[PDB]
């Protein structure tokens, strides 16, 4: 086939069908296609560009050594979500990689919001990448393209399916460090192919001690006896996870970042995937199981629906794009 179960990260449809009456609904608008920026904008080497033309030097060490970090923010109903936290994480990871963006956090925010505004997209997948660059000048690339779904909207509402790979584990923090968001998906791609080979949508990877790590492009949250847990070690410190933990705390639910063993993963009351590109996804079954009754669990539903409500509530988590 040559195609995994992972969403292709490329410019796509401006809207996609979502379940009627569900908490996920795209905005009603039209693109002004006389503007070449309509539908997708990239900012490469200091120049704003139409997304379809966005190109980088093949000699960027961000390619040949994947020597880079990045972050992804989402725009929903014209509002960008937690951009400041994303910029903090991006710059903190770049510092750990000895990468110097050359721009301040405020400058990157302005450029990012400008990419979104120019694209006209009310729902957008927004990437900031900082690479080691080439002759030695580190490079910053930003783009805003139509919204991308790690799991289709239908699975956000009605749940998805997962396996634990028989043949793959997540790279550990002492090898290709997953606590810094990176393009090095060798293990994640391998796990996605194993999932597709086995008829599942996605994979939950373990680390070398058989503790839960994360999935291809998402953190995993585990519900047991009314408590919420999520791996602390070999997993990205996700912003969706952070939001889910804030939501849980407000609902009076105890949420803990800790080691979650493989025993606990298989014994879960509920499982969910959380990531910027699509939010909170119920996981109905594991290794051919229906965790619980095989449909989205009550805590997952409460947290997911609350998560999407935050996208429209004025407050510190969202900033409107000027457009």
Image (cartoon, rainbow, N blue to C red):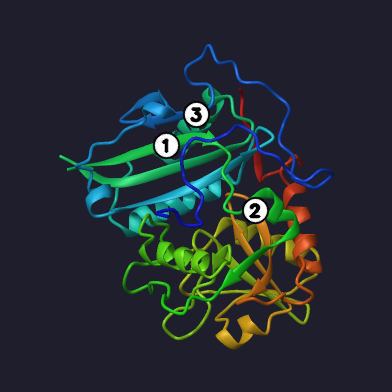
Q: Secondary structure at mark 2?
A: strand
- The x and y percentages for residue 209 are 45, 86
Q: Secondary structure at mark 1?
A: strand
Residue at 34% from the left image edge and 59% from the top image edge: 96
- In three-dimensional space, the C-alpha distance between marks 3 and 2, rounded to whole angstroms, equals 21 Å
Q: Secondary structure at mark 3?
A: loop
- The x and y percentages for residue 104 are 40, 39
- In three-dimensional space, the C-alpha distance between marks 2 and 1, rounded to whole angstroms, equals 21 Å
Q: Is any part of residue 215 visible from this angle?
A: no
Residue at 46% from the left image edge and 44% from the top image edge: 9
Please indicate whether residue 12 sits to the left or right of residue 17 in the image: left
Residue at 73% from the left image edge and 43% from the top image edge: 18
Q: Could you say which disc has been placed on residue 142 in the image?
A: 1
- The x and y percentages for residue 149 are 59, 48
- In three-dimensional space, the C-alpha distance between marks 1 and 3, rounded to whole angstroms, equals 11 Å
Tell me the quarter of the image containing the N terminus: bottom left
Please indicate whether residue 117 sits to the left or right of residue 190 in the image: right
Q: Outermost residue toward the front?
A: 1
Viewer-closest of 37 and 137: 37
Viewer-closest of 211 and 88: 211
Tell me the quarter of the image containing the C terminus: top right
Q: Could you say which disc has been placed on residue 40 in the image?
A: 3
Q: Outermost residue toward the left?
A: 135
Quarter of the figure with residue 316: top right
Residue with the mark numbered 2: 279
Bin the neighbour count of mark 2 within 10 Å (Cα to Cα): few under 14, some 14-19, many 20 and up: many
Q: Earlier in the sequence, mark 1 or mark 3?
A: 3
- The x and y percentages for residue 296 are 76, 65
């Amino acid at each position: 086939t040559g195609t995994s179960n992972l969403v292709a990260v490329e410019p796509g449809a401006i809207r996609e069908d979502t379940p009627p009456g569900s908490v996920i609904q795209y905005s009603d608008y039209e693109l002004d296609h006389s503007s070449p920026f309509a539908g997708g904008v990239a900012w490469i080497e200091g120049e704003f560009l139409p997304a379809e033309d966005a190109k980088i030097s093949i000699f960027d060490t961000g390619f040949g050594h994947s020597d880079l970090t990045y972050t992804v923010a989402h725009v929903w109903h014209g509002n960008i979500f937690r951009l400041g936290d994303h910029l903090d994480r991006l710059l903190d990871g770049a510092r750990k990689l000895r990468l110097d963006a050359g721009y301040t956090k405020d400058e990157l925010a302005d450029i990012t919001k400008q990419c979104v505004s120019m694209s006209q997209l009310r729902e957008s997948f927004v990437n900031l990448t900082v690479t080691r660059g080439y002759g030695l000048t580190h490079q910053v690339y930003i783009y805003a393209i139509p919204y991308l779904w790690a799991f289709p909207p239908a699975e956000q509402i009605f749940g998805t399916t997962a396996i634990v790979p028989r043949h793959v584990r997540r790279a550990g923090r002492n090898t290709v460090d997953p606590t810094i968001k990176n393009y090095q998906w060798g293990d994640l791609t391998a796990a996605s192919f194993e999932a597709k080979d086995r008829g599942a949508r996605t994979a939950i990877l373990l680390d070398s001690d058989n503790c839960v790590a994360e999935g291809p492009g998402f953190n995993v949250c585990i519900v047991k006896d009314g408590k919420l847990a999520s791996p602390s070690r070999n997993a990205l410190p996700g912003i969706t996870r952070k939001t889910v933990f804030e939501i849980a705390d407000q609902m009076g639910i105890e949420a803990t970042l800790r080691d979650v063993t493989s025993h606990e993963l298989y014994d879960a009351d509920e499982l969910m995937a959380v990531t910027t590109a699509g939010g909170v996804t119920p996981i109905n079954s594991l290794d051919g199981e229906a965790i619980g009754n095989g449909a989205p669990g009550p805590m997952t539903v409460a947290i997911r629906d609350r998560f999407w409500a935050l996208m429209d509530e004025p407050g510190p988590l969202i900033e409107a794009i000027e457009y």
